[PDB]
Amino acid sequence: LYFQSMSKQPHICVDENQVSPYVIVCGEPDRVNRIVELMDNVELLAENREYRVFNGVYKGTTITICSTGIGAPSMIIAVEELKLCGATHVIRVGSAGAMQDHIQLGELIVAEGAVRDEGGSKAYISSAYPAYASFALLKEISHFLENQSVKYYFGVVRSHDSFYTDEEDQLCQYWNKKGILGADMETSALFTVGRLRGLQVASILNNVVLYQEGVNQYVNDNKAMMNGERLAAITALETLCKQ
Amino acid sequence: LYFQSMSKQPHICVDENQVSPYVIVCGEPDRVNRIVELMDNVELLAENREYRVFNGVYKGTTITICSTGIGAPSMIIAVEELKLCGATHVIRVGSAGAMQDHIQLGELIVAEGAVRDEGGSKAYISSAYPAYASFALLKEISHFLENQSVKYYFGVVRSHDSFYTDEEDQLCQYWNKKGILGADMETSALFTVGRLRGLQVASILNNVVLYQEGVNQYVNDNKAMMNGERLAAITALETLCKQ
Amino acid sequence: LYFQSMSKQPHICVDENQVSPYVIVCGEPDRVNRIVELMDNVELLAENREYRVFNGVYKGTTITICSTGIGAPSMIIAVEELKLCGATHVIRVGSAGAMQDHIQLGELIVAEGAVRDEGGSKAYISSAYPAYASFALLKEISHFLENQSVKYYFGVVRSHDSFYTDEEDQLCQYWNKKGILGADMETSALFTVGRLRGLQVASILNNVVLYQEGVNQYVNDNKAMMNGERLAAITALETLCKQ
Amino acid sequence: LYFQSMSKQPHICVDENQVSPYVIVCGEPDRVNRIVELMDNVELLAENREYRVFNGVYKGTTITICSTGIGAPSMIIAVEELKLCGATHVIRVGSAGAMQDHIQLGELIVAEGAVRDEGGSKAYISSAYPAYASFALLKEISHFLENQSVKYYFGVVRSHDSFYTDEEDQLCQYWNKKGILGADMETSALFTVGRLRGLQVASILNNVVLYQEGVNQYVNDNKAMMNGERLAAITALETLCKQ
Amino acid sequence: LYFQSMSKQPHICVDENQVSPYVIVCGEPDRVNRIVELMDNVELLAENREYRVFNGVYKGTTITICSTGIGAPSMIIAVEELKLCGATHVIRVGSAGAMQDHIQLGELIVAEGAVRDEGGSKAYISSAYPAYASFALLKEISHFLENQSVKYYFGVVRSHDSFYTDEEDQLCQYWNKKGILGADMETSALFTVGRLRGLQVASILNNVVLYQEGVNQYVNDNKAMMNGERLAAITALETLCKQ
Amino acid sequence: LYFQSMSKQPHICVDENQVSPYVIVCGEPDRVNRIVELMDNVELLAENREYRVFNGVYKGTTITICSTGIGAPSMIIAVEELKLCGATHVIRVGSAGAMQDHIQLGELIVAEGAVRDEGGSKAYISSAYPAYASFALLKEISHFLENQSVKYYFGVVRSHDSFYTDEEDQLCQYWNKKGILGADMETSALFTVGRLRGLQVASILNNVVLYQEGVNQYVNDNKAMMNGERLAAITALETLCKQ
């Protein structure tokens, strides 16, 4: 009771004996339950606010799975606390909204780089500092993905703090013209804070919004999106067990 | 199944038939369950990611209680979607870390104004725009609080995107000297986006960190903090039922 | 002669024996003469540059009236020097240009908050810090105003350093859409610097420009505006004598 | 009465039939009375708020003298309105505080350039735009000054919106190290807005603060300062009558 | 004579018939002559200002070598004009100053990412946009380098516009603590403008300054540095001929 | 060999025994050869990268001529190193693109002031600091130019880091409306860094682009431009020998 407040990180609610060097983070608590379905020797470590923490084993390697909620600030709390617990490699398995015409639902966007349009990373360091993915992880992500059939795209994503501003339309058109693939709310924060803490980082994003329908298509779309999520998770697991 | 995706807001997962004009938001999903204990005719509306949504009745008035997770971006999603569902008055019942010496655990900070050191509100509008609380709500909050015994403080809070930066110490000292009462991660975003959407807004914050111990004191502190949380919730309910 | 330069503040030209804790500031030197007409036991304290300083008594309470000229920088000099002389409560009685269609000439705008689009306050502190009015003063201003007939509006004003830029039209339309009530040049500076110096602050503004005529209407308009000015002054006096 | 509001600029309260192409502006209304003592055929044109407006003749040339109060915003109003009335050449005759050790009271600083640390000019244009004095006026100012005995300095001044911030000491040391001669509140605004309106501009500043005493020295200092003011005025008059 | 001004890019002075899709850029004109020593079928294309342009063949592949002078602005001219001439892959072979203790002279820094502390890239796009190297090129650079003996480092470099500011020491210490490997003046500009133009980009930098000596050591150091330069060039040639 | 690295500045490759107090800088190395044609007792001092350094004598005065390449960063290196070698007066003889309709090719623009839209000067000091030309040099430039026939214009130039951005058209129209005469890439950097180092500075620019043709006109235009360049050089030489 008391010794736990002493031993555990105050948000993710785990300690250095529990956290693997290899971590997958996602926004959605329920996705953690879906990811661990792919793993053996699964155990619940912690449940606190938006942070749901499990361990499991994938091809002989223990990997921690941690939800972080929506947005850079809640991501950053998890990154900092995971690092304190001995994390060394962290892969975001997340969602994005497409910023280009021909990216379909359930296709994958692999963020090589991210536009830092969120305030979280800016609290740490000048926006001029690059948010980019680790080569060692990109190498293994690319090697896995080229050997299967679902389309995927390597490039730049934009991370931001709101898609509900009145200038959303103008932002979308501007960033589409700059060649951005998709947008999320968390990737640039992981890349900036993660790298500053000496972490290897990457982000694999399931596309869940077309850049721009009946019940049937709706069901088809949901299945495509679940398939993309499963592919993203598997890619991250295959990558992390090879480190 | 399909008609719900059509009818419901995509994150808070409720609609205009469900949401009251009077809303309490908090960060912690489990706090929603604790708040509804104070109300009659309670019903669960939605559970999705960090968003836990309930209705209840307090002295004859239906009030919606909604969790929003940690951070401006997840707060802003809830504010926008609640507004779309017909919200008119929104009170944050939250936590803060004290920025002055003599504010004890479980004492209350009522944010009249907030420093916009989070990126969420800045996506909407120049930082020069003021984040401040509505007079009509402050009037009722003050009237309720002056008539009881737990100490409380009206003034400025700072809202930010991370307390884990290496400059945290320097920030704390600078803001203490400027007379800031406490810090959270959400208040300025509610005040800025809320006001721009025509909402009446206020924020009542339980102090959960001293500016600067045995098992006994630890238990005493936890009880003080639970008491503050209950006081903050009651103050918000008493305020909203009087509108 | 010499001992005065020693004793008196270098711009407002008064000292701590002369200044009341309760102060009204306005831009126009001649308005000070008009305000003191409402008071008993009136005396001229100082006249220097744009700073005209008088004391008077209103319902038993000594109140200092001080002109400050146009603009944040000259306002800030007065605020700093008044504070040095023992001011604790300061109310701006000023003019504004309406930023919404149905605010008439001589109607009042009570600034709850102000957009800090002037450089004066920015010399002191990040623009993220809120410029807002003190609750204790707003309470008394509201109580007085609701009990009379001239229309008045509580909300946000914009304070700026020039209405003569070539982008004035675009500014007006943008700020009208954001719901700003009116604009002046001084309010945000009083609220920011004032609050940082521990002052209670508020601002009551006579509307002197329509958002958008014969000699008769011109005379009618001037009388409406003089009436608004008298109402603003009386509201400030009634508020300050009740502290 | 009515036709005047129609004909006159709304602050300086004069029109194009009254204003000379050649204008001296100063901050202090009473200095206008002191300047016109040096001129023939003197007439009062207008008195409104901090704006005191006179015409006079110096060696055959009509020159308008206009006070503007303290600060960029009130300066800018005067500059804009004077321009509307047909001003083409404008010289500030003002005061400064020395930013270097060996500049004495009543010695002159001629601003070739100004640091734009005031918000007024920034409302018009990016701070990157240069605030500098017109060569044609500097030529005549230099020619006059080299032929007399009071020391004077050509260089950079800093214009700002407050000397009362808590960082004043640090600003002073930083700007002294950069070689700035003195500081005022108005010069950069005149140079920026003036030049953008196609005006020839210059600024001659009497030093009234040492960078860093008995009644006798105090009297001596006041006389030195009055002498500097008279020299600055004469230099501006001699310059303007030669255009 | 005339038809050339018509056909050739105005600075690099070549056209689309001359430029290969595969390009090496360096700052120093004389380094181009040193690089082509490693190639067959060498020809001078153009010499204009700091731009020295040659073609050559390396293992069957035509590669253009182009000098760009010092600094982002001259780099950007070359990048834009090369792109206009059909460039698709561009590798900087350059120099850097080490920002960490144990990087020796003539060891290599491979920039995965760059801090955009130069104004050139900022003319194009918000500093939040990432400057990072292309995965396809990093893969081949890494594969080549791991198979030889000279030490090399993958990571972040800082690109800036001056190492002669008075704050240079403070910059060095700050950026060393953030884990930056070295600094140059050009890399972030190539990565930002290059990527926005759809180019594959990378940067291989010879270390020519220790973070912190006799004639003998001086000679040894020069030879180490020439060796590093040759290694960087060969790595770029080996990478480009494999595309 | 070794003692030179010890004695010489590391880029311009000369020392304090070689550099005159009076310096002309230009961007183009080959222009240095063209300038020295106008001088007696000419000697090559150094050739390194874009820096070509010569001395010569003009009417009895030794003057150093130094090329600096394109862009603020390479200019700034030269300015810093020249200053270290005892430079006191520096005149840029350069090229500009006209920003107004009736400035012809080979006519001269004399920069009184410069817009600091380049990052080099911003590394040293806030953009608010003015970039302007020295009066003593402008006086002599004006005196020389008024006594000949080629048209010339005194005013503001804009210095920037790229004319190849997609917003170039919008920049041109905006700056034309603000009254800017022409644009280059170097002038504001010389004026800012130069003045901060205590240098007298000026910039004389040959117009080489119309704001907005046969072989004949092309030849005529080239000759006009060569004539302007010769006039600019002569004006700088005549100015410097008179110091």
Image: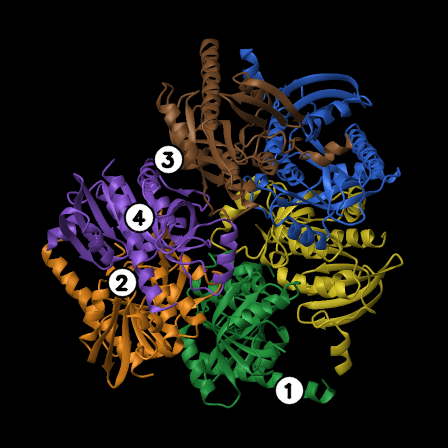
Chain colours: A yellow, B green, C orange, D purple, E blue, F brown
Q: Amino acid at mark 1?
A: Lys
Tags 4 and 1 on a common chain: no
Label 4 – label 3 distance at C-alpha: 23 Å
Looking at the image, is F129 positioned above or below residue F72? below
Query: In this figure, which residue is indicated by the disc labeled 1?
Result: B223
Q: Are marks 1 and 2 on the same chain?
A: no
Quadrant in which the N terminus of chain C is drawn = bottom left
> Alpha carbon of mark 1 to alpha carbon of mark 2: how far?
58 Å
Classed neighbour count for the residue bearing mark 1: other residues with Cα under 10 Å, few (<14), some (14–19), many (≥20)? some
Q: Position of residue C75 (x, y in %)?
A: 34, 64
Question: Do the numbered discs 4 and 1 sit on residues whose CB atoms are within 8 Å?
Answer: no
The chain under label 3 reads: F
Query: Which residue position holds label 3?
Result: F179
Q: Is residue B50 visible?
A: no
> Which numbered circle lies on residue D92?
4
Between label 3 and label 2, give the one nearer the viewer. Answer: 2
Residue denoted by label 2: C50
